[PDB]
Length: 14
Length: 227
Length: 214
Image (cartoon, rainbow over the protein chains, first blue to last red):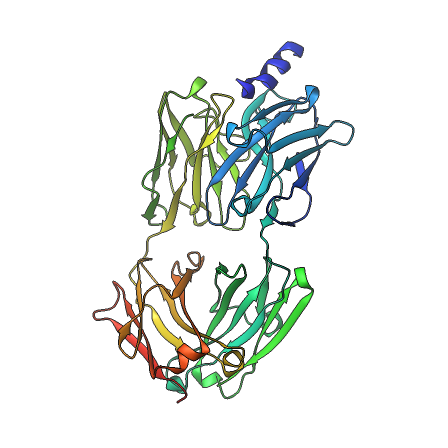
C-alpha cells in the first residue's frame, strides 16, 4: 500500500 | 505548523495542458506523502494521485494514468501537478494535501490521512473568451411602495471566467443581501443575480448601488437600482 | 476499487443535537484506514478523524469515529453552529484512494414560507435582444420548493434556471432565484408573466405577475 510507505520509511529510520 | 501555498487560478482551452504548484513550508518535505484532490463546482472530492518526494515515488489513480504527472523538487519544497489533454470536465478547484503526523509536533510517524491542505487552485477549462459581465437592475416592485418589505437587485449576466464579486453601497449594506451561485449557461458564459430586501419606507430615501467586480477582465461596475 | 456509500446524503438536525453519519464500503477497508473530513462552503476540507477512530490534535472531542471492515461511523455528540456542513469519508487502505459522495448536515428549524418577488426584464437588457425575467423566493425553510413559470397562463418548461444559496448562518433559511430567459422577440409575444410558488409554508400556491410594458 502506497499510503504505508512513509510509515515504513519513518520506522526504518526511527 | 505545515502551510501549503498553491499557484493562482488558471483558464485553459480544451486539449491544452496545465501545471499547478504547491509549495510547502514549516516541516520536512521529503518524508511525507503529498496528494492532489479536486472538486468540481458543487461536487464531491476526488483523489487524483500523490507523490513521496524522497524518491519521487508517485501513485496515480488509474482514471488519470497517461494524462497526469506529479513531480516534487526537494530543493524548493515544491510539488507539482501536470494534467494534459484538458477537457471541460476537468474544470475544478485543485487542492494539494499532506498527510498529518501522530500526536503533537510534526515529526511523528505519518498518519496517511490528509491533515494539511493548500488554499486550492481554480482551473477552468473552456473555449469561451474573457468577458466582463453586463449588469442589469432588478427594479423594486411598485406593488410594494408602502407596507412590508421591498426587494431590489442586480442581474450580472454573461461573464467569463469565474469569479465575480458583488457588494452593496460599497459594502455598507450587508443585511438581507443574497448573492446567488453563478450558473454556467450553454453559451459558455456565467450569470448570477444579487438581491437584497429592504424596508419599503426606505425606497424614497436611501440610494441603493450594487458594486460588481470582475478582476479577470479588470472590470468594475457600479449600478444604481431604483423604482 | 472500493466504493464508499454515505446515506442519507442529507440530514436535518436541531442544534445541540447528536449526529451519526454512515459510510459503507464495497469491500473491506485495509487496516481500517478510514478517515472523515469536514468541509464548509467556500473552504478547504479539514481532517476530523483518521484510522477509523483516531482524532487528531486540534479537533474538538465532540467528534468521534468508529467501525471496521466495511462499516464505519462518525458521531458528533452535540452539533455546535460550526458543525453544520458537509462530511466526507475516505479510505486509503490501498494505493487507489477513494472518497464517499458526502453527507450534508443542515439546521432543521421551523417552517418559514418564502416571500415572493418577480422582476421584469430591464429596458437596458431588452435593447441587447434578450429578456431575463427573475423570480425570487426569499428566506424560506424547508429547502423543497416548486417554482412554475406561466406566460399567458401557459406552463413553461425547459427555459428557466434556478440557483439556491447556502443555508443562512443566522436564520437557517434558504433563498432561491428562478430566471426565465427569452429572446426579445419571444418576450414581446405575450402579455402576462407570472411565477407560481408551492411550498410547505404556504396553505395555497402564491403567484406574482406583471403585464409586459405596463
